[PDB]
Length: 195
Length: 195
Ligand SMILES: [Cl-]
Ligand SMILES: [Cl-]
Image (cartoon, rainbow over the protein chains, first blue to last red):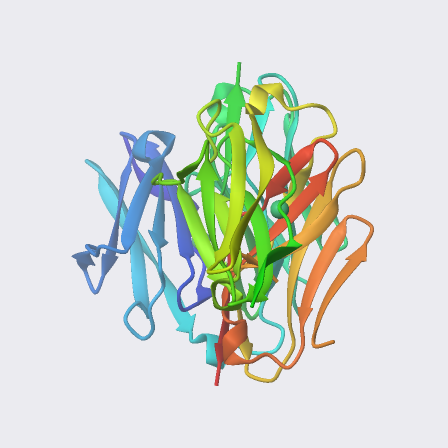
């Protein structure tokens, strides 16, 4: 048996009021660890906060939507535990009002759209984002971070190219643009895969 | 006094199941005419059908959402009337299943997004659409067709550039792509104008 250790730790995020923020945490160990999210040592419990498990519960995403300020601004902790030990890591959420966001904060200029693809064909979700510094584009599916699937960029356009689409690819996709100023989400877009 | 005549008549549309179709009708006359929409001589009444007045009731849009097939496929009539006379014009709705749409039917590759703009500054809503033939991009605001406001194109990108934003510009915008095969709507995007 071995105590938990983190394989991914959450990083500080600065979001915008009305938007989304997500924190990602993953751990390994024997027994396999499970994760809870706390604030000031108490388990999070809020109508606008959702925890989404992955990796049989050894991965977790804390998603906050819609963001409120100052309500949601705090230090949060990801706590990984098994019967051998417990470890935590902290992270900070900042939430700006739309009238407080700096010049340069990411914008989603155009976002992904509803798509129905025939099974085994390629589906490409598209996003255009800008900011200063130029933002990184990442993708979420059903509230979780996403050779068959490629993340492409060209200038402001990001593409999530899903080759050989299969039933498991169906779900709700979001484009996320991040730079040193903060994070902005696109509206969600459903992908359906038809037989 | 003069009987109604049409200044805009609706045109046939081919939409996709789950999407939107809109028909536009406008008339003039003395007294000012008012419009009703019929099918087979009966006033439309359906949970998914909305009629939106403009021009003090002498303009009207019939909006159907979400489209169903064969349910919604029919000939419809715009009927303009005043105390001097009544005139009607007919139009057809076709609704394709997503598994029946032809190669070339318009796609909204990326669509407009939520935007908050400071009053008097420019807001630009963006859309990317493709098809064969290359589709025309039009814009709707609060379910109605939209020098201060410019409709721009560059390759697949359409921009609705709203200069000198004012409170009346706030609302729900949709990009619409149309070619000889049919019509596809973007997801809607809200514009807010803050003081
Ligand atoms: Cl994170
Ligand atoms: Cl029309």
